[PDB]
Image (tube, rainbow, N blue to C red; front, side, top):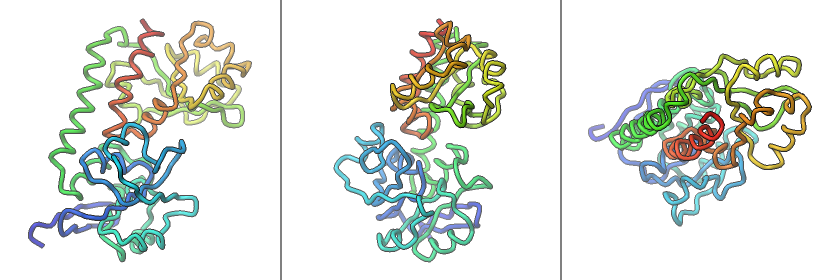
Length: 285
């Protein structure tokens, strides 16, 4: 139709006839893209942290007084619940969507899928861009993406000491005695943009390789969500003998900073640009 918008995604094309009045956020992080441009969803899908409406502090202002339904993915995408919400747009870029489930959601309303072959956690910019298109606010979304990039560029300018310093981004809990890590990729781009060197690392470092891998870094960023989490890591006898532990080069994130890194959104990344550089500066100089 004239006035309509068509977006292209992993399962073909979706046409949105006009600015949507009832948007369902069916994936783990899309609410931040929607809220960034003033589209308040009628449903949000919870991921973690027990936040009100699944909306973390950096997006609460934008939510304001809204009382959206809260969904979850415990038993996959809740198709029947979504149908009952009578949406006119379903955003499911970070929801584990497959072709079958896309077809089912499309019967309910125009549905926005992941752009390529990653059904969860596709590049944040790809997700932001298609959502901005679908809600008729692509100009602002482009600006928001620019704004985030500029924040990290500015961090680099404010902290030239970060240059050439090797960083690892680690999970806040051990898994079967091993360390969880974020391998280089879109998720580590923000660190690279701040001037840091992002070490090659496997997604899981087995217990017998922890010293071998982690002692190669100048700073370790553990995405802890509590004091309980940090003290459990420091209580581990291998972690206790890391060069990073000895030289006080561990960063144990607050819950909000851990959450902000995880969401990697137009609204959450500004929180990372605010709170992470002081922690980096504390340990790197």
